[PDB]
Structures are given as structure tokens and as C-alpha cells.
Image (cartoon, rainbow, N blue to C red; front, side, top):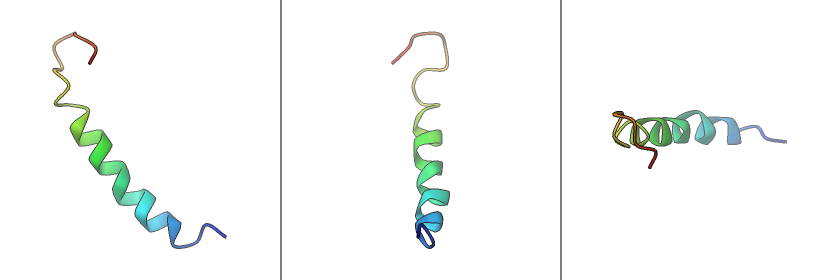
Length: 30
């Protein structure tokens, strides 16, 4: 139950966190 699922979650959480910074870290939302 939710065994290997842990490996995709671990790396797929890098893509969202990296593409979120390109959201203009100035002050505008997105």
C-alpha cells in the first residue's frame, strides 16, 4: 500500500517547487 508511490512523489515534488519560482518572485501572484 503506497510503497513505490513514495519514489514518484519524492521527485515529482521537485518539478512543482522549481516551476513555482519562475512565477515572478517579485510580488505578483501568478
